[PDB]
Structures are given as C-alpha cells and as structure tokens.
Length: 426
Length: 21
Image (cartoon, rainbow over all chains, first blue to last red; front, top):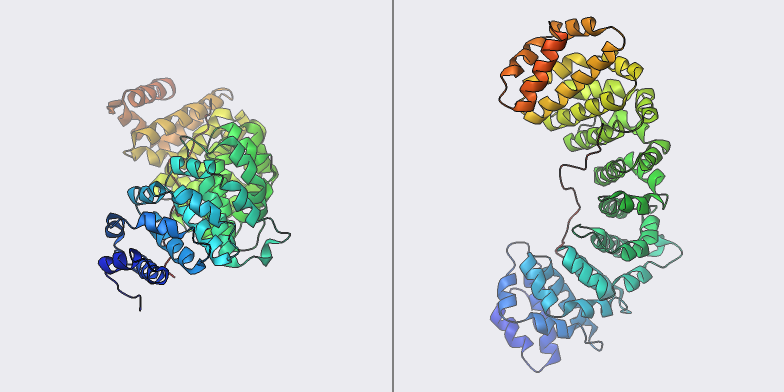
C-alpha cells in the first residue's frame, strides 16, 4: 500500500487535488521517515513537502492526515538543526500548539512529541516554542487528580517535552516559564514510572545547572528529599540525573548545600563512591568535593557519615578522572577544615595515595595535591608535628616526588614544591 | 579558600527522538 514509495510518488499524491490521495501519500512519507536506516529527510525537505504537511495539521475534518503529517514532521524535526529549522520555518510551531487540544489523544501526543524535538534543538527554538504559548496547553494536559489515569506513553512524552523546555543555558529558560512549570514538575517527580522519574530528574538537573538564584527556585519547592530518595534508586537512568541534580545543588550556597545534607544524602555515598559505574563514582566524588568546600559543620558531617575512608579509597584506586575529583575533595577539605578534622584525614591514610598521585602527568592535579600537602603541614605546624609528617611523606616515596617537581616546567608547581622542601625537608 | 566547582562535563537526556512506530 504505502510501503517503500519514492519521493516523486509522494509528491505526486500530495500535489493531487484529492484529500484521500494526499492522506495515502502522507502516510507513505511517514513510513519512509520512520525507517531506521537513513530516512531521506533532505530529499523530502527539498521536494518542498514541509509546507504541505504543515497545512495538513490544520485539517480538523481529517484527523488521520493530521496524525500522519504530525508524525512525518516529528521525524524531520528529530534530525539535525537545519532539519529542525526547516520544520519551524514552515510554520509548524503554532500549528502543533493548536493540536495540543485535539480530542484525539494520539494526535495531541504527537504534537507534544514534535514540540519536544523543536525545543530540544536549543535555547532559541525552546524560547520560541514558549513565546508561541506552548506551556499553558501542555500543563493543562497534566491537570488531572491522579497522573496514574493517563496512558503511560502519553505521560512519558509530556514529561520529556517539559524537560526540553527546562533544558539549555545561554540563556537559561525564562524565569516566569520556569516558575510556571515547576509545580507540575514536582508532581511528576513523585510519580512511580521509571521513565517519568528519569526525565523529571533530568529537568531538575537542567534547572539547577546555573547561578544560585536558579538553584534557589528549585530548592524552595522542597524537592531535595525526593531527589535524595531517587539517588537510592536501582535504575541507573534515574540515579544518573538525580545525582547530577544533587551535585548541581551543592555548587550553590552553604545553605542550599545544607538542605542536601539535612535530607540524608550523605548516607547514600558509601554506595555511590564505590559504584561499579565509573561515571556515577566520578559524579559522586565531584559532589563530595563541593560539600567539603563547605562550612566546618558540613565537613564534620562528611566525617560523621564515615566518608573520609571512602575518599581515601577513591584516591587509592579509581579511574583517573575520578581520582582527580577526589584530590579536589581533599584540597577543599584541608582548606576549610579545623586542625582536628585535618589530623583525622591523615589518620585515615590520606598521605600515601596522595603521594602516589604526584606521578600523574596532569599539571592541575599536581597543583591541587601540593596545595593539600601545604594545608596539612600548616595544621601540623600548629601542633608542632611537622617532623612526623615529613617522615611519613618520605617513607612512602613522597619526598622523592616533591624533590623532582622542582624540575617541573610549570611555574606554580616547581614553586610550591620548592617551598615545601626548603621549609619542611631540611 | 575553597571554591565550589561546576561540573566539568555536559550531562543530559536525549535532546530529540525519532518515532519508529
């Protein structure tokens, strides 16, 4: 029937003055466009079919051609930016928004999907979709007493599309749009479907990826406890964005960071910092590094939750990028910590693995580690214990590495090392 | 003297989706 049509035959059917011939040809186009191997998107665009598809979106008396055209355009918009632009340039945005209110659930859903692809292209198209008034009708589709009454695929698509309206920066989405969307997002974040939860977490991770003011908008909605709960989920597609969101939040103020701690986030970290998925371990360690950049009472919570041994662990053995985040966690800890907290660090065995990493080629991690060592020595100075530390560092081959770093070509490195040598190793 | 650091890498869900059926 409509399987494997040539583009010329599709054009012929669409240019016929016959609505049923146009429907068949549009369906043929939809099938070409939904084939996994190189759908001929550019050939379809070149044939000038987008404006025709867009006009078909308005055919209220022929819902089948609305659906087929909506599907065809969705798949063109799913392509490159240039391909998405062709769809927008054809006037698709207002046409799809009008379709959100369709009495046909499958058509409304397709329009949600298409708008998701358009918004997903970038900040400009996202903002243009918002300007055409998409948010109101989208939110209206979710204005039900219990989300569980909605078709699963339908809910997932709405969640995903809303996440794209939250996505991207330079600029971030309009403050008013974010305020408008958040209460619905908070609701979706409490739903029970893993895909809805994952995409709700993605949206929250985008919204918290910015200045403290953007973080505050989210934190004020009280979602942190739910994020921490999702941090403990078994589904990796949920934990990944949940953890990015939590990590973003702790890049904010000390107070915003405290809400994460208050919600019990630290108790999940023994598992996160030993997680078999490398990226989870890395993001969790990054997150830890920002928490140890906090107040002394927050560093103390890290101590109380027994997380210093886990940091020693990651520093001792982990993917290198993870070890780098650990190094940062330690330097931040030593920067803001009390003498007793810093001493505890040494007692947990931080020195040897810290020394071992000085063989790294990465210039920045070397600077970070040397800073930590300087900080630790400072604490020791205030206890008259520099000698015993000097010996510790020498016993594990640390002094050898620091001595060599005087020959390091980077200025700040061969400076910092010289300073340590001439001040504690004479 | 500890400064907070934003993520080094972009992390996001799928920006666009093709409908297969």
